[PDB]
Amino acid sequence: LNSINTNAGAMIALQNLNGTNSELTTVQQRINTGKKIASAKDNGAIWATAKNQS
Amino acid sequence: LNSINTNAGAMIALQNLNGTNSELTTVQQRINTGKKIASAKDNGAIWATAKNQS
């Protein structure tokens, strides 16, 4: 398929790039916070247990 | 038949030339649009499915 209207390979390449960007953003947050569960979005059960313990 | 009023060979040649012209116009459309089914006339059912999917 030598189409000029679509480019599927670019689509999968962009999906992979966004996955890498998401992983990098997660690592950024985990480094500048110092905690792997800094909010309820990280893991709700352990976050709630840690809030109660604190 | 050495007639001077009727020229059947010219008629057949014109029909063949018109067919070539139509094929060339179809290829011109398929190049400048980039679509083999750019309208309902090219293929009604596949064009309908493509409109719904888009």
Image: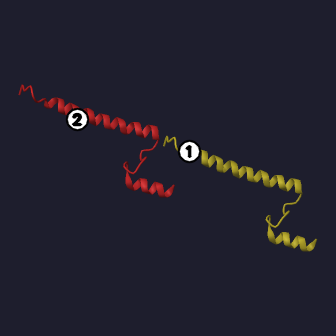
Chain colours: A yellow, B red
Judging depth in this view, the residue of B35 and A11 nearest the camera is: B35
The chain containing the residue under callout 1 comes to: A
- Say which mark, if any, is on residue A7: 1
Give the residue drawn at x 64%, y 46%. A13
Give the residue drawn at x 83%, y 52%. A28
Tell which tag, 2 or 1, sits nearer the viewer.
2
Residue B50: where, in percent of width, then height?
Answer: 46, 54
- Say which mark, if any, is on residue B15: 2
Q: Identify the element where label 1 is drawn.
A: loop
Q: Amino acid at mark 2?
A: Gln
* 10 Å crowding of disc 2: few (<14), some (14-19), many (20+): few
Residue A52 located left or right of residue A17? right
Residue B26: where, in percent of width, then height?
Answer: 37, 39
> Vertically, is B28 above or below B53?
above
Q: Identify the element where label 2 is drawn.
A: helix
Q: Amino acid at mark 1?
A: Asn
Give the residue drawn at x 79%, y 55%. A26
Q: CA distance from mark 2 to mark 1?
A: 40 Å
Residue A7: where, in percent of width, then height?
Answer: 56, 44
> Vertically, is B10 above or below A28?
above
* 10 Å crowding of disc 1: few (<14), some (14-19), many (20+): few
Residue A4 located left or right of residue A51? left
The chain containing the residue under callout 2 comes to: B
Q: Are marks 2 and 1 in contact (CB under 8 Å)?
A: no
- Give the mark count: 2
